[PDB]
Image (cartoon, coloured by chain):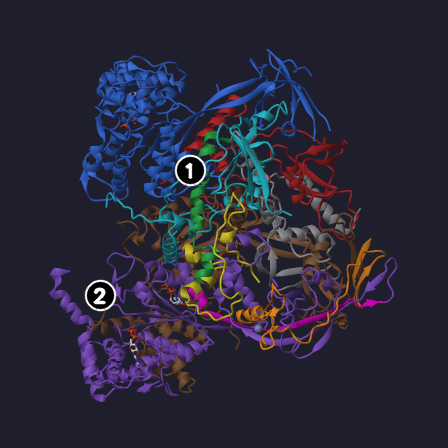
Chain colours: A orange, B purple, C red, D cyan, E brown, F yellow, G blue, H green
Amino acid sequence: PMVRYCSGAQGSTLSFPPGVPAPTAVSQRPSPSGPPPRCSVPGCPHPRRYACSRTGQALCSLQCYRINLQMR
Amino acid sequence: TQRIASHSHVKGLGLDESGLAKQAASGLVGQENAREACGVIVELIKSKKMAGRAVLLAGPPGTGKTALALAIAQELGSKVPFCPMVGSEVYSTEIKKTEVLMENFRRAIGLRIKETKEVYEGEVTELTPCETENPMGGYGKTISHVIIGLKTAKGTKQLKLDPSIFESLQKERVEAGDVIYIEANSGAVKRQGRCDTYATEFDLEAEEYVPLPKGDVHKKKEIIQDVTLHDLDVANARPQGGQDILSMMGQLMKPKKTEITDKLRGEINKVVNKYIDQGIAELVPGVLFVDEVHMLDIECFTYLHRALESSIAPIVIFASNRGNCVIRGTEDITSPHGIPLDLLDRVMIIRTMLYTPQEMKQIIKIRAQTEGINISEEALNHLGEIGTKTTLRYSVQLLTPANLLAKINGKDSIEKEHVEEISELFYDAKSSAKILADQQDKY
Amino acid sequence: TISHVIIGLKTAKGTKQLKLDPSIFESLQKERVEAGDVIYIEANSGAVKRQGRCDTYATEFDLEAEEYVPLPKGDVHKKKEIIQDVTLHDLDVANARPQGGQDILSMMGQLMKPKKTEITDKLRGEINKVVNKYIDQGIAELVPGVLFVDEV
Amino acid sequence: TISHVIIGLKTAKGTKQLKLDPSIFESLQKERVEAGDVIYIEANSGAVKRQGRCDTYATEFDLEAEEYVPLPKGDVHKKKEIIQDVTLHDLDVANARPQGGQDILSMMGQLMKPKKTEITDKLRGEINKVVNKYIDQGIAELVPGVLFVDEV
Amino acid sequence: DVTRIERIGAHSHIRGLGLDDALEPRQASQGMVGQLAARRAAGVVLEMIREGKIAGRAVLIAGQPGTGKTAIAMGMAQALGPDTPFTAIAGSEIFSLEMSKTEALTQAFRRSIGVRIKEETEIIEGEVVEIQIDRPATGTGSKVGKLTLKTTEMETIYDLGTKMIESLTKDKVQAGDVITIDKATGKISKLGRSFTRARDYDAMGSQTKFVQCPDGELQKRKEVVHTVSLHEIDVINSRTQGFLALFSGDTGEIKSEVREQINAKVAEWREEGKAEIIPGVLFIDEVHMLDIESFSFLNRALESDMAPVLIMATNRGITRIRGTSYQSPHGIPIDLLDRLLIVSTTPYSEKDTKQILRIRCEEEDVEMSEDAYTVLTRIGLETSLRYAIQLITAASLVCRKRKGTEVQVDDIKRVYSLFLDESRSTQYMKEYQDAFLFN
Amino acid sequence: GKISKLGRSFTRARDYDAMGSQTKFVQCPDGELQKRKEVVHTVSLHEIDVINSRTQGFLALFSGDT
Amino acid sequence: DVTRIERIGAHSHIRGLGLDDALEPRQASQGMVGQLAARRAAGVVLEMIREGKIAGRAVLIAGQPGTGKTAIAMGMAQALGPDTPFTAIAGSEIFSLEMSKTEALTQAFRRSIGVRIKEETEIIEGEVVEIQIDRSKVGKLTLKTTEMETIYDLGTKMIESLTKDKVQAGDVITIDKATGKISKLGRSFTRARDTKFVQCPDGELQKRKEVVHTVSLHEIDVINSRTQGFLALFSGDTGEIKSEVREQINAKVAEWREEGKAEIIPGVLFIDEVHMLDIESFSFLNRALESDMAPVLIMATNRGITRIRGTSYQSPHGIPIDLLDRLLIVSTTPYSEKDTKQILRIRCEEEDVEMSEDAYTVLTRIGLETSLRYAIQLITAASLVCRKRKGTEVQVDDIKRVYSLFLDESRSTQYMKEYQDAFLFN
Amino acid sequence: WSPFHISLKPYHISKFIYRHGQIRVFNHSRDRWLRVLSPFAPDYIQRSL
Amino acid sequence: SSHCKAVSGYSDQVVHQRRSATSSLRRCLLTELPSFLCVASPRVTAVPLDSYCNDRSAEYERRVLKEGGSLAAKQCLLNGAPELAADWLNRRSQFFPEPAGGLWSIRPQNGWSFIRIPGKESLITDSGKLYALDVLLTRLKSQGHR
Ligand SMILES: Nc1ncnc2c1ncn2[C@@H]1O[C@H](COP(=O)(O)OP(=O)(O)O)[C@@H](O)[C@H]1O
Ligand SMILES: Nc1ncnc2c1ncn2[C@@H]1O[C@H](COP(=O)(O)OP(=O)(O)O)[C@@H](O)[C@H]1O
Ligand SMILES: Nc1ncnc2c1ncn2[C@@H]1O[C@H](COP(=O)(O)OP(=O)(O)O)[C@@H](O)[C@H]1O
Ligand SMILES: [Zn+2]
């Protein structure tokens, strides 16, 4: 149960014994999305500040919230 | 636009190659002998040989002694320190006068040291603990190094790092999508935050996002920094660290100036001597200008006594405008300029004389033009006559209100009527004193 | 929480096991005391002093920085009589801004700037009563002296 | 997990039930109050004062460190109309420097000795504005008092 | 070309007192000329201080302004040496807002009696080859390791305990480094990276200077000499882990009991032969400024067995003592004045003023003609010597302005006309009676 | 991303009959929710001095401890 | 012989102010004599103090130096006795560095007026016989007095309270029921076989004891200042108590008095050497003596018409007329031959020296010619000389010898005029 | 050698004083109004800002 | 000027070798003040004063004060920060732990206790015979004699 760390002449080395929790892990890049989300109203080109509650659609401001409320 | 001060026009002494003083150059007129002496003093300061030499500009009020010090400062440049002071700065409720004076003396001596900065910075993409494929006796593997990919606005590149840095990576929160930076000389790792690119994947995130770095992943530059010798004193007196109850306790308490012991200076001098001998830092002596010296104390003068003959003190320029006055701190020991005779034998006296009406008119014109004011000759002559009647300051001060009155009347320049109206409105010292003397019974 | 500390002390005569207050454990953890390190605890104030590892563990490490002291001789627990010369002003100043004890208030008061303070009459009177009680027990002996004021 | 706590008060005039937000529950837990104690609560201030265990449990143990008090002979619910006075200087002093926020169970009030300081004018102006706002809301009213000076 | 922190000041030419083995002053030696009697007395007191057997001795130097009293002080300071403590304090460097006058004088006194300690330790200077760390998995926090050191001749492998490993990790020592290990205290001083081991390197994790390999045997002995004043020992022992007060100067009015404890402990230290106590010299300049209470404290403090050989300096006459209304010689009460020897200085002449000017020019690297020297001496006789000394640099600068090489009488006359003397400034000052302030 | 609690709504001021140590009842915000605009700040130079005077100097602005 | 902290001082021979029930003083009683017209006027002030009905009264004792104006004020404290606060300070002790001068007078007034309360406590005192603690925990112990025994079952808290303070058999212990503190007094003689030896207690194990307690008003003010305000009450770290706190505490004490929940005990403030006290302090006193909670103050002045400190004005006693109207003046008179002789007799009794009858006349003459104090201090020197002589009784020839060694002010000043050159600044 | 160790009897505070003596205890309902009227409340800060 | 070490200043160092008796001289280097200098100790020590009331609430409060008001403040004043305390707790598994920032970081030479055990080397400096023997031994050892 000994974790060995050797700073040798040829280079560093970190060893892990059998069955050690080997905390050393890896990482990756999650896939990104191309277009950012947009306001659900087709006329409004602003991005999604938030999503509505009563009906559940992307919204930007007071005007588009009122538009979505009226059109439903 | 930068606002007009009271000494904005002074840009230099205006001397020839032979040191002779021009009649009017760099915003200064007259005082030819004083300008020549100040040029000699400038050469002395640039000589980098003497130390603790003092000059006293003596003259009546409003004759330009303060202006000549600023002219010397301008002609010196900006790579040499120039510390102004009045005589009332010594009187502190936090520390003794001879330490205010010693700190100021150490302020007027500056350093200039060069160094290189090397950093690997950028967005992290992946962390690959590349292994050597053949663990050693009694172990299941042998990690050789860590491959870290970093990308900036220029490009992406992979760096091979010591495995131990991983132990630091888990100390902070080192996940993909963050921007990091590692100092080449130090070797530590620090996290700045998530990129702006992923700023839209949520609607409310507790962390603030920083923009993606622009430029090469590995930056390396050379920087030269200038620190005065007083900054080293304060830095060494109050160690700014956080891993202590003392450091943090003092950093929570009200900060107070402490009388620096002479042993601290004795070691700072040794280390700066060593680094100068190694050719790393360049020493540049400067100038310390005390105006209104007559406000000092006899204890302050007696400390200045010993302070001047030091081999480290910078060049000091004193200024005063007092006649045969009583020295501050004594009862009736009168002296010229309010300065003790024994100190006054260690200074070189530069005499400053009055101003002739032609030079006064030239000064008024120079001030008007620098200020952005147009004046007619029939009004400029009247203003010069009024100033010669009372003083130069009272003539220069009426420039702006006359311009405002003319602009109110719509005219683009000052005439006789504007000057006479402004003079009728405001008063000078002499007429006010006459009124006070006349009406002494009702004050 | 911690309620007891079990400590085994081995002198030349032998070894004994002791149960001690958790404050002693706090002091021991403060001084970084492990097994094999000679220690010396006093029970009047709870102070702990570490003198280093034992002389037996001398050849364990080729390179080492700790100093080694020999195994103490005598009993594990022992009482001793100490004769001390003091003044009233020492007791007064010690009770003014206390520094004894293993707590955090006095430990951190040990580090602050030692500023003098104006002692009130109450502390002087209480010290007088305490020293009178000590005198009545046949232990405290009073030896008033001389104060020399020059250039009065 | 926790939204509110229901408590039942009882005297020798009746019984009532109360609903407490987690702050008051934390205050009760700090006082080490269990089921069967005589408690005093002020709704306006949120003050919690434990007045000791009730006498009926006095036989639970022969020797207990606690002190026992009789069941109160009075109303559980008490209403009064109280009129409070406070001068501006109290507000200036309270808001000038960080309020200790220590009412025991803290050694950090044992570091800095309080000292009287010079109140800035920005604070005084803010206090004036806040007082104007609150007396405009009708909550409080203002009274111009009198200052008296001897040995002027 | 390079300019160090030390420049050419007013007393930068005096390298000593200029005395022979018979303690007879010379006319011109080591930057000092003239003033034979004062130089003799100064040599006597310097030999007395060097012997260092009697304590609490005071000497006053009196005379005209600008006659070398401070010059004599600097001369004996330079002749004393660097290893003997010397403290120069002005007359107003004790009136402090942080401690009382008596406390300041006590600190000044205790700052002069030095203690010299020779500290010999066993050290290991060598190049790092590899480092072995075996972290425990769980256990109880016990760590084990090895460390291999190598020089150009010999190499070895050392075991590691649980104390130096944390220090090595804190200093972040890796392969290819040259380190000095202190066997006694256990500190690790970093020299630099080697050359050959730098070939195999990862990305930049340590970029700094370069060094070579310590030749010879791996284990050696180092020696340091520490000179510690009594005052800083007092400050150290006045509070736990208090060391920045040496530089910050925050300790104020230290308790006396600490002072007697330090005195006793220094006595035993001297007896055991470990450390050596050496008395020093305190130089209070312009001491007329001291309040009467300071003088009377000096009275008693000079009778101790640890007081230093304080040297006074005054240029005043029959003047009232500061803080009182009683006249007295040198502005000092007779009580203190009756406890010390008084050395007086005589005004200078032409023959030695000329040599003073010559040695000043030699120090400042300025050449003048003999007629220029005569004119300068006439100026430095009609007017004080300091003015003539000051005019040298201005004349040299003016001569260099016209691309000259030898200063001439015309340059000196030009400088005399440009700057001013106190007498001439006062003369020109009387004609602007109404132009000045508060006449 | 910093939360600044202002208190509780007026309509929510009855579910507790014993209020805690410090609570305040304020009216519910009106108008648009996420407001983005430009503001002007007039700060004296003395404040900028005091802020950099020490590590946490903004207390001295009201305390007068500078 | 063990030496107490208190030894033979200058006023250690005074034990109370001797007067009869009709307030008329007798010639010799309780160690102090003389001043017939001063002891009677001091009795009225003492009765006023012991009453406490009226508040804010000032009395000033003025007279020649050495005429007992400090002696009668020192005996007044002894006659008043403890349990009534008495704060005596010098007039030059209020000029503090970390505290204002006006605040020191207020801090001194509030040390003299006290607040007294009475409460009830439950105390368990007795000898323990056996303790048994099992392995919450169950405990049982049997206490035993000389008149009863009782077994007790312990709760969990009492288990810790008894384990912290190791209690064995045969220990006389006292326990506060409301708190849980174990305060052992000693061990009984019965278990001494095989460290203060106290006998077993008497009466019931559980006692309802009524305890009275008094606390200074300044003490109350200081407790409320900091987190732990009592700590600064011993080290003096308190400074500039806010004036708003004092008003609230005064209102609290006033309503306590009105409700009968506590009582107020007026005290005495003795201020010595008032003649040196700035006009600011005097003006503050003019207004601080008109408060409801203003104690009674005795003040002593030995000066005549003199310039008052802080100004260039001259008034009697070195005190402005404004403060003189507030107070009442008692004047002492110089001692006579018989009074001086009796004082020397009393002193010689105090230091316990047996000296001859023929020495009293010469000592009285010396005292009458030398302000009566030099004779008082000559006695100890004469006794030491006689002890060096191996004698037993002090004779005349052993007094004059001392009269030649130690000088007085008049003789030394006379010997000073003929050495004028060697003496400084005259 | 070790320094002489002293220990004083604890200072005694009665229950009447501990119950009705702290201004911090008998003025909690008055300090609450000072914290309500403080200008550092987040409501006032946001409103003024 | 580090806040955790005792640095006197700069002083030249001489490093003597064992072979060929070559002595190398060093330039100005940071010098640590010798440890032994700290020898002072107060005459008397006192437990901090504490109050005492007669009810369970005040007893609870003073028992809290006897071990610190809160756990958070206790680890703050003992390690620098609660997170620093957690770091110190879990540092056992770290090869390169971050330096501590609390009272455990401060380590005076004599500790917080004023008890001073008589040093063994006093044996030399109390007897001249021992002194002699010591120096003669060093001599004979150098020379090589048995
Ligand atoms: N040589 C000069 N050339 C131009 N302006 C001058 C000159 N000398 C003085 N002045 C003007 O006089 C004004 C006041 O002079 P100042 O330097 O204050 O005199 P003093 O120092 O004697 O008070 C300045 O505004 C400056 O513009
Ligand atoms: N004997 C001497 N040898 C060399 N230089 C001297 C001598 N006497 C005086 N000087 C020079 O005169 C200058 C002024 O002397 P100073 O130290 O001011 O005398 P004082 O301190 O007595 O007024 C000094 O810079 C010094 O170099
Ligand atoms: N009536 C008295 N009875 C006994 N002793 C007295 C009396 N009056 C004065 N003394 C003596 O005078 C000494 C101090 O005198 P004091 O009262 O201080 O003088 P003053 O009244 O001028 O202050 C004391 O030692 C005391 O023994
Ligand atoms: Zn939209």
| 10 Å crowding of disc 1: few (<14), some (14-19), many (20+) | few
In what element is the residue under mark 2? loop
- Is residue C15 found left or right of D123 in the rendered image? right
To which residue does mark 1 refer? D80
- Is residue G175 found left or right of B441 in the rendered image? right
The quarter of the picture showing ligand 2: bottom left
Residue G339 in view, yes or no = yes
Residue occupying image coordinates x 45% and y 77%: B78
In the displayed structure, would residue C97 be above or below residue E158?
above
In the displayed structure, would residue I15 be above or below residue B367?
above
Of helix, strand and loop, which mostly describes the magenta segment?
strand
Q: Chain of mark 2?
A: E
Q: Amino acid at mark 1?
A: Lys
In the displayed structure, would residue D123 be above or below residue B14?
above
Judge whether residue E340 is colored magenta: no
Front residue (pair I124, B20):
B20
| Residue lying at the far top of the rendered structure | G147
In what element is the residue under mark 1? loop
User: From which residue to which does the magenta span run?
Assistant: B103-132
Across and down, in percent, residue E312 comes to: 39, 55
Q: Amino acid at mark 2?
A: Phe
- Is residue D52 found left or right of G53 in the rendered image? right
Front residue (pair B201, A55):
A55
Across and down, in percent, residue B367 comes to: 30, 82
To which residue does mark 2 refer? E438
| 10 Å crowding of disc 2: few (<14), some (14-19), many (20+) | some
Across and down, in percent, residue G93 comes to: 34, 37
